[PDB]
Image: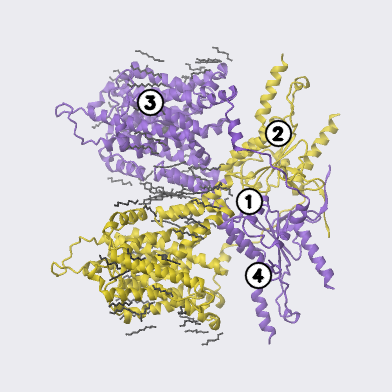
Chain colours: A yellow, B purple
């Protein structure tokens, strides 16, 4: 083994700078930087196409023998859940369920072309559907007057058509906003969605879905709520009118709920013995339709059912832009929430599978999906969190599984929709609630973060509470800001350490940590692992004066008290020699006799104007009582901050900067030795 | 001169830990910490009294011969401006001007006892007065019905009394809120008001005052505005109805404005020849009253005047708590803004005079002043920024100058108020606008910050724009949040440096800076002066792969391409030896041949779970291509973050940590030498 051997002079800043000559920066002109960015080599255009059409990259690289079985199983398992979720979330959007089926077909196909994630399930989302239904009923209330040429027994078809128009308009506007944000590179903000924040946000979204499904589980009529405390209002309303529940709807839904839970437990426990998981949503739906049609519950027990599902696809139709001025705010909110839900879950799966997702491409894909789908009578979509978990956890590899699920939805739309007309809405509710279980499993993060980082546990809990009680829009921005403020908290509560020296080395460690490091007599070394900006500087100065035990104000007060008791451009030197008489020093209380204070700046990333003022004050106050202050390990950035401020207006302070703590200690000891040499 | 000499073994983490034994922490029980905090020694209670009654400290220490002349001159100069400001801001509060005089007397006396700043002028403030007038006219509109037993020629006395009741109620509530915040130690938030933020905020407040004075300068009638864009609305309204201006009011106000400007220029230019500045506000007021009374403008030209000022003080009266539920929101806002204005200017002067102000004591003093003053018919007060500048800049030392100014106000209240009844409101407006000049001088900060720190210039401009276009309440919190987010920006744009070694030393500096430092062959050293948390980790990894020129993905791709071209608990080792055939290596493109990458962690303050995942990925990806990754200079906090996460689940990574960059370089070179020794 070799050894660490260093033999060099003491490196103060002027001494080290004498050995360094400034290098010539290579010319980097902006005009040439733009010119070299427009070469348009074929590889560059191929990379651009891959960026904007990801299917052009991962489809030719499809490992058929390694991906086809997993994609097929995942596609079937995703489709059997996609159908009831589409119907239920269409109900949440105040539109006929067939439009939820449309929203489960076109955007998934488009996302298979434009999307970057290969595990999320694109489709209707409960929170987005709730927002769409809110704007739809605000623009088209239940007591609206329509001169549609019908008798007093109105079938509510015209009201449904008007609400569909409103939903398509808001969907087109939200898609336009999402596409514009993706073009303007707004997706960079996805970097501010940390893992605890994402998981707390998604758990809160799952609670939102569960709350939105309660009225359909119980069969009660409840006013629509959207905004702050909407989850609380919805739960309160459902519990308030729970006395008017449909007992048959609740019984059927609870039977489906229990059977689904049992089947999911069976699948999980026998995963190793089952070649593929049994699709239980298909059996749940079919059995439900059998029970409702066979006993004819729809009017026998007034059980709410899915209703008529017209067959066939609709021709493209232009949404009316005339409603934009009435919906744009909602369109903005839906755009934001849709992005936040899509990029969160995507990240959650990408980190699980060792790849990365482009936020800008996610925004572009969402915008194109929503805007083009609005032409095909599709309301605003997002990522379905529970269905994304199902798709990922059933062996899903690429987005071809989503294409297979969309093919199943298309089969329902074209030929077999009429078979589900008697399916009870309660059954749909139960299915959704059951599939929320995996989402709720994320609560297991609370102990884990409690063991790993209480700051990140705070981020998790704050994000959960915010996204729950406020909306998924206001709660998300609140959580992002608070998570960023945790960094300010970290800087405002740093580790203030007094350093001692490991004998016969140059290693300086916390004096209260290892029992072998010893403080150097006459020298105090103070260290902060944080910047010294405005929110920090006063705490840093107080901590220095408290932890080192060297308070210049206390020293001055003791000097004055001892004096009273014994009674019965040019710059002055920074350190004023203590002209304290020895006769008065006889009454001076004993102390540590510290002549130098070393400030360890190795971990100080930056210093602002307020921090520079604090540092100058520290130097002046300590020099007034005849104590030297040295800065050790100042980075080039910190030295530049000191120079941009008026810290080195007196050039003498250049002598206070040393390369390392050992350099400063050796320089201080050398200064003391020279002072003793010239004393006598 | 001595020399830097170090001779020791290479300090990897296990080697250094072998030399260190954990020290025993001294017992610090919370129960004993509370017990020692309740000793109640006489010095402790004296310090408590000094904290809560600052006058008990600085008054006995009053240097009479050194303070009396400055305090007297400052008191006269402050009072002559305090009278017109009180009248004008009472007009802004929709209350009779005598109540502004009351608000200029009691709170100043109380703040002389409870306040910590010794230079700010306590009294009515234009923004606080505008908020008070807004709530007063909202609760008591101009078209209110009062059965007061009067004829059709109502004198608006009952409406004024009702508005006074509303103002007193909101003042009492705001004072209670301020006192409670001071007790709950909310004043700590004053640490988040940095100097650029404070100066931008105060400049925006000055613009608010100037805007509020315009209608009285021109004599036009304008609807009250309060809230977002209130300054824009007020300026637009004044400019809209400027065609109905009173030409006589504008002429008198402009004459006073010009004479005041000339007098202030004379005072500034002849400060060295004048024993004391000439109080020009007194002459401006007196002359104005002479012109208005002598020519009898009040009805001859319909010039708005101050009006009747009743003599004598009012007995204490309890404000009606019954209005609290109607005003509490406004009371909250007024409490916040009043604090923000008071603690900002206070800090601005404390930093100017080398002392410090307690934010909690400022909150307590403001709350007591407002709550007690509401009993004496005083509406909510704050610090007057322009008058504080006048008081500080005229030789003010303590708050006895404010007491003298209050004595002048009391003299006006008791005996000589009737003399000012004909004083034109336009004159008051002009006086206020003139005294805003010093505030506007703060715009000179823009070039200064442009030269010192563009981040702090951004803070200044953002605070100014926010506090101007939004209110002083919403703009302030927006500015505080954005100023804190500048730290996030700093962490997200750090200095990524490739380090080279200064020959014959252990100094490692940026390779592109000094032309004497040389990169060590086979070794890449990468440094970031920032933490590696979630908002940083991806950028840090990309910057490492880009700046070092060592991209493991590019290496793997080149290896595969060369292979194709040539064709025509136990853990595995972290670094996989490159099993690349030499025959295939003949087609391998030439490279730097880097065997070790050193990550400089000396400036990394903390690392979160996302950053630890990124670091583990970096280590794994570089080891997959047979490249070692070393961490140099990891702090105890960073090592603890790595340990709390599952970074050292494989104990082998403990060997990747080195005390310094030179330690890591020597260890890497030793590893390479040993590998060559065992090769053959
Ligand atoms: C920095 C710390 C204190 C977090 C700040 C969170 C801020 C940005 C949050 C918390 C409460 C939020 C408000 C809560 C409710 C509403 C009403 C809604 O109709 C419009 C948005 C609005 C007005 C929100 C705006 C954003 C808001 C003010
Ligand atoms: C970087 C910073 C600005 C991020 C946080 C900004 C927050 C604090 C700002 C941005 C937008 C602001 C809102 C904009 C408009 C209004 C309406 C007004 O009638 C009450 C205040 C309120 C509701 C503001 C509250 C504060 C607010 C939410
Ligand atoms: C053990 C000392 C640290 C404890 C940290 C606990 C963090 C709890 C955060 C709760 C946030 C709730 C937001 C409403
Ligand atoms: C192990 C972590 C020590 C700190 C625990 C307490 C963390 C509290 C974080 C509060 C952040 C507040 C941001 C507004
Ligand atoms: C020279 C490159 C840096 C320039 C920094 C200029 C900062 C301007 C900030 C403007 C903020 C305005 C808020 C509305
Ligand atoms: C000399 C300073 C270099 C940086 C100049 C540009 C500063 C821009 C700061 C933007 C902060 C944004 C916070 C939301
Ligand atoms: C940045 C997102 C908004 C892009 C502009 C959309 C404006 C609506 C289109 C005009 C229709 C009248
Ligand atoms: C990606 C395919 C987009 C096809 C869009 C066709 C829109 C036709 C509108 C016709 C309106 C009458
Ligand atoms: C997010 C930027 C605005 C989004 C587009 C708004 C379009 C409003 C149209 C109003 C027409 C009168
Ligand atoms: C981002 C491109 C979206 C294209 C969808 C159609 C946009 C125009 C709507 C119809 C206008 C008549
Ligand atoms: C924290 C500031 C508010 C303190 C509580 C004030 C509540 C008003 C007093 C009750 C009057 C009805
Ligand atoms: C600091 C002096 C406070 C005096 C407060 C007296 C309040 C008297 C109220 C009488 C109401 C009729
Ligand atoms: C800032 C905390 C609240 C301030 C005090 C509110 C008092 C409201 C009284 C309502 C009475 C019905
Ligand atoms: C913080 C103490 C303020 C005291 C002022 C009086 C508070 C009570 C108001 C009158 C209630 C009847
Ligand atoms: C606790 C939820 C709110 C109250 C729900 C019960 C309302 C009355 C039911 C009879
Ligand atoms: C689901 C079968 C049981 C519930 C419905 C029948 C009994 C109640 C009728 C109102
Ligand atoms: C596979 C779909 C089976 C649907 C069962 C219910 C059919 C009702 C026919 C009356
Ligand atoms: C993605 C393929 C879309 C095809 C839509 C065809 C609609 C025809 C309606 C008559
Ligand atoms: C990550 C960016 C979050 C932005 C939230 C904006 C909410 C707007 C609600 C209308
Ligand atoms: C896999 C299902 C593909 C779509 C079948 C469409 C059948 C239409 C029958 C009218
Ligand atoms: C609302 C239901 C919450 C269920 C949490 C279950 C956590 C299990 C972790 C093992
Ligand atoms: C709101 C419900 C929270 C329940 C937390 C339980 C965590 C269990 C992890 C084992
Ligand atoms: C080891 C136990 C960790 C518990 C942390 C979760 C607390 C939840 C409070 C809401
Ligand atoms: C609004 C109150 C914010 C309080 C922040 C406390 C931070 C403590 C850092 C030591
Ligand atoms: C530019 C300020 C707003 C317009 C002021 C002029 C309004 C019309 C005056 C005749
Ligand atoms: C200051 C101007 C005095 C003369 C004004 C003449 C015009 C008066 C119009 C009401
Ligand atoms: C010092 C105050 C002088 C006031 C001048 C105006 C007096 C008007 C009397 C009619
Ligand atoms: C600070 C002294 C307050 C004295 C108020 C006296 C009021 C008397 C009214 C008759
Ligand atoms: C420094 C703390 C700023 C808090 C601003 C709160 C504004 C509330 C307006 C009602
Ligand atoms: C310096 C002025 C002190 C107050 C004088 C009060 C005189 C009252 C006369 C009725
Ligand atoms: C609104 C008036 C602004 C005046 C700025 C003057 C700055 C002078 C700096 C020397
Ligand atoms: C809004 C007016 C800004 C004017 C800035 C002028 C700065 C001059 C400093 C010398
Ligand atoms: C040296 C010139 C500095 C100018 C910075 C101020 C720019 C003001 C833009 C609003
Ligand atoms: C809302 C958009 C915020 C953009 C922040 C950009 C920070 C750049 C750091 C490199
Ligand atoms: C190389 C073609 C891949 C599939 C492209 C489909 C049309 C965008
Ligand atoms: C290299 C294969 C390109 C075509 C893939 C299949 C497209 C339908
Ligand atoms: C590795 C893929 C082999 C099969 C190619 C596709 C055959 C349909
Ligand atoms: C989800 C794949 C189809 C169903 C397979 C069931 C195997 C027991
Ligand atoms: C995705 C559900 C498929 C339902 C099929 C019904 C029988 C063709
Ligand atoms: C309330 C209905 C009771 C019968 C169904 C119970 C299902 C577990
Ligand atoms: C093992 C799951 C049992 C579920 C019983 C029914 C719950 C509603
Ligand atoms: C349609 C077949 C689904 C199950 C595939 C795997 C069977 C071993
Ligand atoms: C063997 C599992 C049966 C599950 C049936 C579920 C019907 C809803
Ligand atoms: C799922 C099969 C239900 C059969 C019900 C028959 C009632 C006549
Ligand atoms: C009114 C409830 C707001 C919850 C916000 C939580 C932020 C820590
Ligand atoms: C932990 C820092 C939070 C500061 C927020 C701003 C308070 C005014
Ligand atoms: C030592 C007394 C100073 C003045 C106190 C006045 C009453 C609080
Ligand atoms: C030591 C002087 C105490 C009294 C100061 C004056 C109080 C009116
Ligand atoms: C030395 C004490 C001076 C006290 C001055 C009091 C003036 C009211
Ligand atoms: C240093 C103060 C001397 C004067 C004391 C006060 C005399 C009235
Ligand atoms: C402001 C002190 C009183 C006025 C003095 C004027 C001296 C020319
Ligand atoms: C503060 C202004 C004083 C005005 C005095 C008027 C003549 C006694
Ligand atoms: C508009 C009035 C003009 C006469 C006064 C001018 C003062 C400078
Ligand atoms: C030296 C100041 C001259 C002021 C002239 C009048 C401006 C309105
Ligand atoms: C009342 C006198 C004010 C001026 C004091 C200073 C005179 C030299
Ligand atoms: C010599 C300065 C005279 C200033 C008079 C101001 C009257 C408003
Ligand atoms: C300031 C003196 C004004 C005198 C006006 C006299 C008019 C009769
Ligand atoms: C609507 C104007 C808001 C200005 C805020 C400025 C924040 C940078
Ligand atoms: C969603 C954006 C949060 C604000 C980040 C600002 C960091 C410079
Ligand atoms: C019964 C009250 C419910 C509050 C909201 C829970 C999510
Ligand atoms: C458990 C549900 C039973 C429904 C019976 C309907 C006749
Ligand atoms: C004339 C428009 C004025 C806008 C507000 C300026 C402060
Ligand atoms: C400067 C304007 C003077 C007006 C006098 C009116 C009598
Ligand atoms: Cl979901
Ligand atoms: Cl002011």
* Quarter-of-image position of residue B58: top right
Ranked by sequence position, the earlier of labels 1 and 4 is: 4
Give the structural element (helix, strand or loop) at label 1: loop
Disc 1: CA contacts within 10 A as few (<14), some (14-19) or many (>=20): many
Q: Are marks 4 and 3 in contact (CB under 8 Å)?
A: no
As drawn, the label of residue B552 is 4
In screen coordinates, is B216 left or right of A486? left
Q: Can marks 3 and 2 be said to lie on one chain?
A: no
Residue, disc 1: B605
Question: Where in the figure is residue B216, as x and y percent of width and height?
Answer: 31, 33
Residue, disc 3: B373
Q: Can marks 1 and 2 be said to lie on one chain?
A: no
For the point 76% across and 53% down, which residue is it? B16
Callout 3: CB less than 8 Å from ligand 14? no
Quadrant occupied by the C terminus of chain A = top right
User: Is residue B386 or residue B441 the one in the foreground?
Assistant: B386
Ranked by sequence position, the earlier of labels 1 and 3 is: 3
- Please report, as a chain letter, where disc 1 is located: B
Question: Where in the figure is residue B522, as x and y percent of width and height?
Answer: 75, 66
Residue, disc 2: A574
Name the front one of labels 3 and 2. 3
């Amino acid at each position: 083994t070799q050894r660490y051997y260093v033999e060099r002079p003491i490196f103060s800043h002027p001494v080290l700078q004498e050995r360094l000559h400034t290098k010539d920066k290579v010319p980097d002109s902006i005009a040439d930087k733009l010119k070299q960015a427009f070469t348009c080599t074929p590889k560059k255009i191929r990379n651009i196409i891959y960026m904007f059409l990801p299917i052009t990259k991962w489809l030719p690289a499809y490992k058929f023998k390694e991906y086809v079985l997993g994609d097929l199983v995942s596609g079937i398992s995703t489709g059997v859940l996609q159908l009831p979720q589409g119907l239920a979330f269409a109900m949440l959007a105040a539109v006929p369920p067939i439009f939820g089926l449309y929203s489960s077909f076109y955007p998934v196909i488009m996302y298979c072309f434009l999307g970057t994630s290969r595990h999320i399930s694109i489709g209707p989302f409960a929170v987005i559907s709730l927002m769409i239904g809110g704007v739809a009923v605000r623009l088209v209330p239940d007591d609206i007057v329509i001169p549609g040429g019908v008798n007093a027994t109105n079938g509510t078809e015209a009201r449904d058509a008007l609400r569909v128009k409103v939903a398509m308009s808001v969907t087109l506007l939200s898609g336009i906003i999402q596409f514009c944000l993706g073009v303007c590179r707004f997706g960079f903000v996805a970097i501010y969605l940390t893992e605890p924040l994402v998981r707390g946000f998604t758990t809160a979204a799952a609670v939102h879905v569960f709350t939105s499904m309660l009225k359909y589980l119980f069969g009660v009529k409840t006013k629509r709520y959207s905004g702050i405390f909407s989850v609380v209002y919805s739960t309160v309303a459902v519990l308030q009118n729970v006395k008017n529940l449909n007992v048959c709807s609740l019984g059927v839904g609870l039977m489906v709920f229990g059977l689904l839970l049992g089947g999911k437990e069976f699948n999980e426990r026998f995963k190793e013995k089952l070649p593929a998981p049994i699709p239980l949503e298909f059996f749940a739906v079919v059995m439900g339709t059998g029970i409702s049609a066979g006993f004819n519950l729809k009017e026998s027990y007034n059980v709410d059912v899915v209703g008529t599902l017209p067959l066939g696809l609709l021709p493209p139709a232009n949404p009316d832009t005339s409603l934009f001025h009435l919906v744009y705010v909602d369109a903005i909110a839906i755009a934001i929430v849709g992005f936040s839900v899509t990029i969160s879950m995507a990240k959650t799966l990408a980190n699980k599978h060792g790849y990365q997702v482009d936020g800008n491409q996610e925004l572009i894909a969402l915008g194109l999906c929503n805007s083009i789908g609005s032409l095909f009578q599709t309301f605003s979509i997002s990522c379905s969190l529970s269905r994304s978990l199902v798709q990922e956890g059933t062996g899903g590899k690429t987005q071809l599984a989503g294409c297979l699920a969309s093919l199943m939805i298309l089969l329902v739309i074209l030929a077999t929709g009429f078979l589900f007309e008697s399916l009870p809405q309660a059954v749909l509710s139960a299915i959704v609630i059951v599939n929320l279980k995996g989402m709720f499993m994320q609560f297991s993060d609370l102990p884990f973060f409690w063991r790993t980082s209480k700051i990140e546990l705070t981020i998790w809990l704050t994000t959960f509470v915010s996204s729950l009680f406020l909306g998924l829009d206001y709660g998300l921005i609140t959580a992002v800001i608070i998570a960023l403020l945790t960094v300010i908290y970290r800087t405002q509560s740093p580790s203030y350490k007094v350093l001692g020296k490991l004998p016969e080395t140059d290693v300086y460690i916390d004096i209260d940590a290892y029992e072998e490091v010893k403080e150097i007599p006459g020298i105090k070394i103070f260290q902060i692992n944080a910047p010294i900006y405005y929110a920090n500087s006063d705490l840093y100065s107080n901590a220095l004066k408290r932890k080192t035990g060297v308070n210049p104000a206390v020293i001055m007060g003791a000097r004055r008290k001892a004096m009273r008791k014994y009674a019965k451009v040019k710059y002055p030197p920074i350190v004023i020699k203590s002209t304290f008489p020895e006769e008065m020093q006889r009454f001076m209380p004993p102390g540590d006799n510290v002549h130098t204070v070393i400030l360890d700046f190795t971990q100080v990333n930056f210093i602002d104007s307020v921090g520079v003022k604090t540092l100058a004050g520290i130097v002046k106050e300590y020099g007034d009582v005849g104590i030297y202050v040295y800065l050790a390990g100042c980075s080039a950035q910190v030295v530049n901050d000191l120079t941009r401020n008026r810290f080195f207006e007196n050039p003498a302070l250049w002598e206070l900067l040393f390369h390392s703590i050992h350099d400063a200690v050796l320089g201080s000891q050398l200064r003391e030795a020279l002072a003793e040499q010239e004393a006598s």
